Amino acid sequence: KAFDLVVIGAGSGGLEAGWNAATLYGKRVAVVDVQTSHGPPFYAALGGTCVNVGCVPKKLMVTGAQYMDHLRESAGFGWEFDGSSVKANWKKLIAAKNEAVLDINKSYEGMFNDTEGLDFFLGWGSLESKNVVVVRETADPKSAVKERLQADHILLATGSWPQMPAIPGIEHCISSNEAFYLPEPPRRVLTVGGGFISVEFAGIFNAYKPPGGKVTLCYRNNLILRGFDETIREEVTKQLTANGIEIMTNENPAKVSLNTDGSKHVTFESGKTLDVDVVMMAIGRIPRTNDLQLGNVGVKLTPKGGVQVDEFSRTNVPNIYAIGDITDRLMLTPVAINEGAALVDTVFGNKPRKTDHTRVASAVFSIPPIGTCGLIEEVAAKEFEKVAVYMSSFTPLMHNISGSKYKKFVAKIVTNHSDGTVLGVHLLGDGAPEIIQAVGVCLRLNAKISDFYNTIGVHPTSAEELCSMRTPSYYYVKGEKME
Amino acid sequence: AFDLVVIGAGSGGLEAGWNAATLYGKRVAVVDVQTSHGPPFYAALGGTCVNVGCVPKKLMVTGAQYMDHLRESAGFGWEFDGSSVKANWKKLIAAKNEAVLDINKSYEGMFNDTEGLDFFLGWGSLESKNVVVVRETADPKSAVKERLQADHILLATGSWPQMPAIPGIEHCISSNEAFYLPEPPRRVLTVGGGFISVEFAGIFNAYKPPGGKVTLCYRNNLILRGFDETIREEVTKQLTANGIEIMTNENPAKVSLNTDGSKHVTFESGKTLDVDVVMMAIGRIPRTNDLQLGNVGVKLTPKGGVQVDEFSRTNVPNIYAIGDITDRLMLTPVAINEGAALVDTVFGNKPRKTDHTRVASAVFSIPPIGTCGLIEEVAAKEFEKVAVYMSSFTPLMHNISGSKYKKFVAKIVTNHSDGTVLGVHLLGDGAPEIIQAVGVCLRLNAKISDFYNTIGVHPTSAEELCSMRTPSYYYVKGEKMEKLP
Ligand SMILES: Cc1cc2nc3c(=O)[nH]c(=O)nc-3n(C[C@H](O)[C@H](O)[C@H](O)COP(=O)(O)OP(=O)(O)OC[C@H]3O[C@@H](n4cnc5c(N)ncnc54)[C@H](O)[C@@H]3O)c2cc1C
Ligand SMILES: Cc1cc2nc3c(=O)[nH]c(=O)nc-3n(C[C@H](O)[C@H](O)[C@H](O)COP(=O)(O)OP(=O)(O)OC[C@H]3O[C@@H](n4cnc5c(N)ncnc54)[C@H](O)[C@@H]3O)c2cc1C
Ligand SMILES: CN(C(=O)[C@H]1CC1(C)C)c1cccnc1
Ligand SMILES: CN(C(=O)[C@H]1CC1(C)C)c1cccnc1
Ligand SMILES: [Br-]
Ligand SMILES: [Mg+2]
Ligand SMILES: [Mg+2]
């Protein structure tokens, strides 16, 4: 049939775009996805990666993982129970997560049923012609044509996909996609990658591992979580270690084979070896463009595989747009959502708007978690003559009593010292993701450190640290650190 | 002889003291009655918050939270013998005691490792407008430990629980004794609808022995006057859902010791109840008496708090009052801000006034409140058109947790004329942490569109603040309605 807009991918960005165009601009909209509910074989489905195999399940599972800390920490506050009766039933967690995800899948289905002028098509979308999306049975372009959709405008919103290194024994390794469906919690697991997904999963597995289990995280580079504040990177390495995770830095899997008992035998380029039940590859995500047959319309790609866009999410081909991870800009659900909103307003509203990819509040659901917004000091040091760093690090009192004396809360404010303007705020510790949200609004309003210090604290909180730093800890002048 | 003499080594008194000494190389004496926490005088070096307020309360509310975490864990697949679960109150109090003592010791450190700054022990009162007398007791006619000369005198003696003069008030405790109970009460009546009564009901609720019952009574119809109405009704539910009994329109007429040591409480409605503890938390009042304010003519207010202008100045030159003795917003960070402003003014020659508007604060209820600025009722009497944005969802984790009663409430009250945020009110896990940076937003004159144009952090409760674009209703010239004309 004929549509004002065809969206390929029913994810974070695609549903924002498709709903807005139908409901706010009264366009006739078609959206395509490969599955109506979560899990094998295509993992992402109606709802997107975040709903099905990202933010949503992972948050529920980290929340589950956090009770390992609460059960132990309760004792400092005089809670007593039979420690030897304690089991982390991973099957109950997964079943709980699956229902939660299926409920979302179902509500999106009902949304398509209940919303006139917004139509779902199941299967594989690809570009036939610059105004025709073909929906097929499989990813294979030979496969049978379920639909052919005439389209004034086409939005590519197919998101990203885990990266698997071409090494021998790749086949004995999983991504985060399979991790969400492990039938049993691995006794020993290697997470491969120093990024948020490896770290967040190392925490999940560490809490639900059967007795005498072990979690190992490996990263090629010296220090996990590049892109994050360096003090936070080092402090989070220490606090993961304190909770019994083995962080193997400057190490990479050369090869995986099977022990005769089917457990996975890891050889690191360093001549180290490890035997584990699971190797989870979390080394990167690449934009999903192969199946889109973008050759048929000549949509400009990067070598990486990303769809190249201007600031308004417009491709080199007019009437064809891309938003979300497929653009390989910032791979976060609220950024994809913002891109979809901004696009539809631009194209169908004539309310021209670009997404601002700077000063984007984000979190890592590590144990403990990270909250961050804006520049780290190294980046700011290259762009500003004078950078001030305000830093407060302290084990909070609750965590003297709790027994987790290692759980130091870190708060860091990075400023342009020439005028006090806050460039970056970086938090590690319980509450960090909740604290940082309204800090996003502060940086949109060009808050200065005097706007933080002059704000009266909420006490007792971790957050009030942000409002109690009067004096820099150190500086960068012309890119050079100075204590 | 001292540049500054401070009566009270509390939240307000120490900030002024340390700032004066370390920023303006001034010479400061601080008076308090006690060097560490607990009986006989409860407050000590560090003040009410450190010794018998925010600090031990937050530790004890954190303890209480484990009752919820242990239950909730099951939804995520945690399995243990529920029948083995015990709440060792005695452990909690010992742990709290050690935590507070370390802070008492931390503050003694500060006075030591700080030149000019020196602690004097005993009771401050005013002899003359430039001489403080540290006595041995709260009797004006006890020995004179010291005579102190003062170019400037700061009054920071804080507040004190009010005990309603009913028959058998000697059988009741304040929050002061609640912190040192040797055993957790099985039956407890917390008297009052304020944050202290509500917080303590939560604590007693988690540590009560088996067959236990926490009852909260309030003299009027709805707890937490001065907080957002939606939140007041919601907290009331969630406390009920967690087995706390809320008695509204009820107030004790008297208390009698039963022969077994328990308390027979007779209400005004004629209702009775037996409880192991009656904790009165009906209000706190400024510690004005033991200063002798007849004896230099400092003027109190129609409510008993030291009268101050915006610079914390009394009618008497050289004499200031900050914190709870001023009987305004009884919060530690307000005391601290006042003290910092006073010293930056008087000694720093950088005059600065505390902003008593747009103050972020919290109730460590289970679950907690975080709030900053005007509730809609107040806004609606000041602004022609007021918009209320409201989102109330049980967050997903509390589907699986089994605590479906834990609804997160996010309210933004705006000036609808220009969209300026007047108030933000949160109920739910994380509300006190969420609200701090909301305080900064309101100082920067954040509009509702600064919130909704900010990209959310997903998944959080906080991101709901950045997802509200459409008012839920309005007040127009004081009048509530779904729609504008
Ligand atoms: C483990 C994990 C955890 C994450 N955690 C967070 C977090 O906590 N917070 C956060 O903000 N971000 C998080 N992210 C990132 C977030 O999930 C993504 O940024 C976001 O989902 C991308 O939205 P999008 O619209 O670009 O694509 P997606 O939401 O991934 O949507 C793409 C959709 O397109 C479909 N599709 C693909 N190809 C085709 C085709 N040819 N035809 C039809 N349909 C197709 C897929 O089935 C999928 O549903 C996480 C990601 C992962 C993997
Ligand atoms: C149970 C409870 C919980 C609270 N929780 C919080 C909370 O979570 N957050 C929050 O912000 N606020 C909270 N508060 C309020 C907070 O404690 C006060 O607002 C704050 O302590 C007031 O500071 P201040 O400087 O006014 O006096 P205080 O901190 O009370 O200091 C006054 C000091 O003066 C001393 N003193 C009195 N008379 C004399 C005298 N004649 N000579 C010498 N010394 C004297 C006392 O010993 C006391 O140490 C709570 C209060 C209570 C009671
Ligand atoms: C996707 N991502 C990044 O690209 C990180 C490099 C950063 C720090 C911007 C991410 C993940 C979690 C939280 N924040 C950001
Ligand atoms: C002390 N106090 C009040 O007097 C409340 C009535 C208010 C809302 C102004 C308080 C307690 C906790 C958080 N905020 C404020
Ligand atoms: Br590195
Ligand atoms: Mg439809
Ligand atoms: Mg000294």
Image (cartoon, coloured by chain):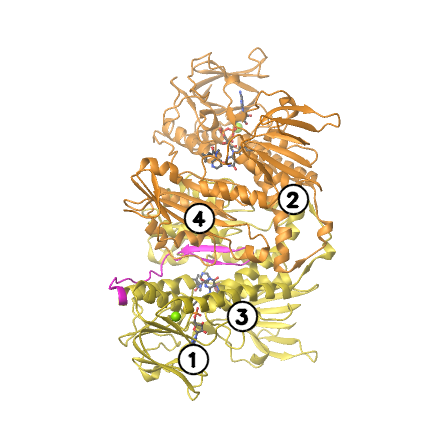
Chain colours: A yellow, B orange
Q: Amino acid at mark 2?
A: Phe
Identify the image quadrant of residue B328. top left
Q: Amino acid at mark 4?
A: Ala
Q: Using the image, name the chain to which the residue with label 3 belongs.
A: A
Asked if ligand 1 lies within 8 A of label 3, the reply is yes
Q: CA distance from mark 1 to mark 4?
A: 40 Å
Dots 2 and 1: beta carbons under 8 Å? no
Q: CA distance from mark 4 to mark 2?
A: 30 Å
Provide the residue designation for mark 3. Answer: A176
Q: Between disc 1 and disc 3, whose residue precedes?
A: 1
Category of crowding for the residue at label 3, using alpha-carbon neighbours closer than 10 angstroms: few (below 14), some (14–19), many (at least 20): many
Q: Can you tell which mark lies on residue B410?
A: 4
Which residue is the site of mark 2?
Answer: A77
Q: Earlier in the sequence, mark 2 or mark 1?
A: 2
Q: Are marks 3 and 4 on the same chain?
A: no
Residue holding disc 1: A124
